[PDB]
Length: 257
Length: 257
Ligand SMILES: [Mg+2]
Ligand SMILES: [Mg+2]
Image (cartoon, rainbow over the protein chains, first blue to last red):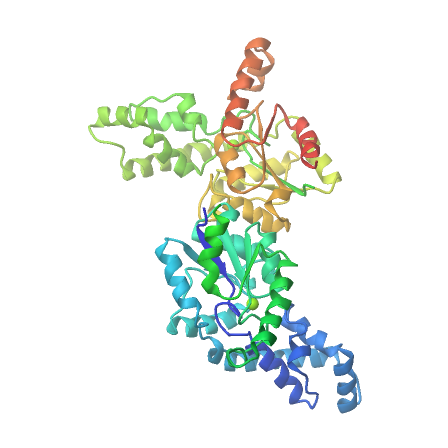
């Protein structure tokens, strides 16, 4: 029944915790004397990077500190400058984050043995993907296909990218495919596309923790942050939720019944 | 609640009875000394023309007959040569087969007034569609969008052409879309695409009759023939069947329940 799986990249296939973008946002602001925190930076983490910047700009705590520094509120120009800067720096450090999350690689190898097709979608622009893809391929990960918002009329949560995938992998109907992500948007897109939607937790952009703080965090404390997200997923369309990609082939078996 | 209807072209919105291709398919095989029937000729109607030729040669009755006549089964060269002929003959008559089918236009206008998007797919190439759609426009018919097999990995039954219509019209999930066609391939395309499928009988390729033959036919014999096409459509995936496009609107309403 299930013939292909569509994987997200950031916080799913690579970049444990999806920090690359978070790292950048904090720089462009810190360099301007208006330092923001990982929470409020990740706060918007789901919309157009361009608008993501503007959102941070209108965040009262940030908006006030900006006005304190520049003696004036951000200008549509500032947003446009910070955005240009955001990209340049991102292209710079993207490769340092294109490492396949330890769990994943093996899982992909297993699915491929079951003749199951591997596809993907993303929030990253084609420019950025060329970079992340190239590094991830040297590091052992390379899905059968890949699509970016540049390939379609609009990105997530539209199912456009997912249809492009099915079109290229040659799989139909939509319910013969699973969508695996690490964010609310990943869930929406999955459903909008009429396919089985699942959500990874450990290393998600939702759980927002690094491999470091996960391995060295209070069990009871961590076992609690995991629920705030696993629940968070189901509350958005996740037919299922998994702490790690190690539970993938298991959910498949379930689904196929 | 439905939001868009994807119409096939020949035998659905134009060319009553889908006659344009018919004599061309029979002619190309007749020149090789291998006669075929209208039934055989019409069986794979709806598919990308090149595929349609390949489909005819695949036919046991025809293949055997070909093998018996030439002492070897049909070749790729043969298929390719006949196709070249098929295109020459077709192109010189295509303008004469773009007249909208009678009451279709009134239906479209109604659909638009209800704010419903109009998309379409076909078996004709983009070059063929250029001629057909141009003439169709002049005669009052022009959907919001058009997609040929040239625009995707493959033609019918694959749901690729429908997904592009979804992308363009900005409609999701596929279940919010209805597919209307006049052949078996039309039915399969819709189901594969995960959308409400409807087949139209009078004027369809499956019925294979002219307007004359329809109005001047033994009503008892007519209803009887209607029953075979209908049973056929359903047999092949059709969710509902209608005699004419006038019934469409009603079917939509039933579905919205
Ligand atoms: Mg992600
Ligand atoms: Mg047709």
